[PDB]
Length: 291
Length: 293
Image 1 (cartoon, each protein chain N blue to C red):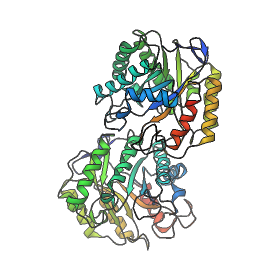
Image 2 (image 1 turned 180 degrees about the vertical axis):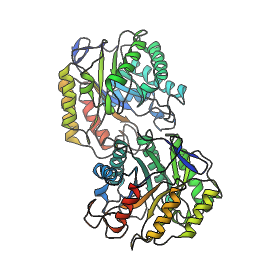
Image 3 (image 1 turned 90 degrees about the vertical axis):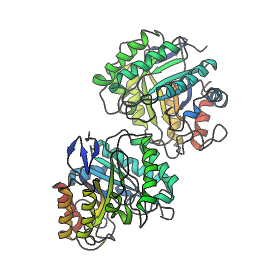
Image 4 (image 1 turned 45 degrees about the vertical axis):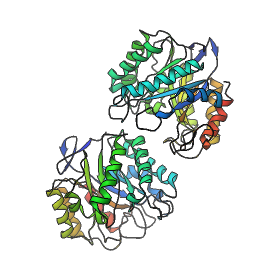
């Protein structure tokens, strides 16, 4: 079993203690996107045996115009999610169930269908963390994200009242400072912080510091060692600064991405696996093992 | 009236004869989960006229942290159970009173309260079958489920001495083989077997075969035609393999679920009912209609 997660002030506690976790985020689960082969019990087990990962993020694709997402292949994506959630439970790992969207607030009925379904099927496990809106775009925290979040949080809680729910923030989950000015009044809510080391430096870390100062807890559900588009070289200086910032604030995180697509963010070289890591995979392996 | 159910060896006898029954299982009764609307006398009557069902399972939700369950809305869930139980008696159908839990052993006071209440109100009827623990998870049969079971069976039996009691087994009620190695010394006890045709195949029937060969009777109180999680396409051939295994061994069963949630396991389309069946609903109707009821 894993320890139950709760929020106290700007800290996420596990079993009442200050600590944090690290693991990999799987790439989009979308049919046709090439990462379907990683949504397996074998892959979840390997994240643990190879990297000593304590969590895994299932990025379930959503989008009315996004090919192979939940709007096109509900069954395929939901079956991949089920396999990963059950494996995480079997491996004593946390599983972040991510509604991987950039438009959740405009396709609310689908978001509610997804969350009521996951709360019903997996809510009883303390391993389950709900990430309700991956990356809102340049929208309003108070008028667009917050109302959607309150609605979804309440729908999940009528089924599964106990859990940690992580809510996306404006501008690809960078505006945690804006969200911190008007937090959501519900128990155990944390806010999403996303960054790519090759593009987001100190000023982005300053925004996160403002959020912590304002009293909200952060969860870096997605971050990369390369540039923001998921490619380019590994920026060790910035990666190390962000990791130190997370370590000294008990901020948990998931690296993008356990995949083999031909781009720098992939943990594996194309067609490769755990024995053939990319420059990013090599750095991530050390970070997760030393967490 | 219906015939009295008893157990002899690995068989469940009805009026002393080998036979089996089929029907639908309602979805969680929980307040706010969208299936409360199905817990009606009309639904019980229609299960009999539309599908020839000879039983109906009432999945009364339980859970200390399961929203809308008996722990949060006792009266609402109990009232829904009452409506279904009385209608089953009025329609000469068996009713499986299911304490729909994944944590009954850890909330015994609630289980005892529930069972003493149901045994007092309905124990006089032979239509009543008690299912004391829907689906235990990764727990021990000898150390966790069995002691809980003995306690609950004794509380029920001090009020209603005659009845069939079905006991959950480990790993979502799959480990009937494990339970068969250390059976309960109480009369008329059967053990729960659950499976989903799109996920569980011959290896799971082999575990059930081990249990039957070891001397215990099984009752498949919950099963699906699609994948284990409740969604997906109907696996016709696997469903047929399981129905043949049940027919030949006279194993009674209840299909999950009489509901309209948009998932493969629902018998009905969203906002639908008897006249608007899903692919699973059509297959289940075919099985129940020709079972013998």
